[PDB]
Amino acid sequence: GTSKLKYVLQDARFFLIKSNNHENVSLAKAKGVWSTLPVNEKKLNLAFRSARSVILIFSVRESGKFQGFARLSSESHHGGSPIHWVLMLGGVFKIDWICRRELPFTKSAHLTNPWNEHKPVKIGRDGQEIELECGTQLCLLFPPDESIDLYQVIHKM
Image (cartoon, rainbow, N blue to C red; front, side, top):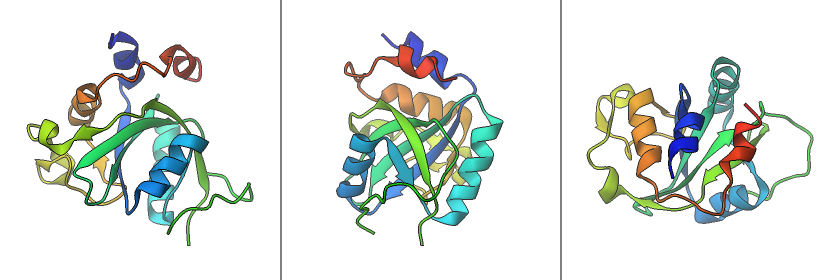
């Protein structure tokens, strides 16, 4: 079901992450981390302290889909085991995946983001914040990922 998911998404903040390649998203999925440019790092750190959940929604450029979404579990940190991104980067955020399944853009055509001029939510620069109701509904469109137990994620928050 979707009830724990809705609980996790309650009063969350949402950010679009655009990746130039699948290899980086695959790495993020395996390793539970993300790194972004300083401008977005600052926004994410601010958002992590401000909200019960901060959700990253991932899209690989030119793929025509979202590849999943994850919750920030920490602020960014520096000096750790170097991640071999296929690329100046900020620190590393730990993340917990909520959904590692794909969603085609064809399925989110009805969702517009008030924070990017009410353009379809698929449209946006890396780090674009997604407004609460748009973001919530977007996460709810994804196929449920039955490999993830959200109890574990709830126990952080």
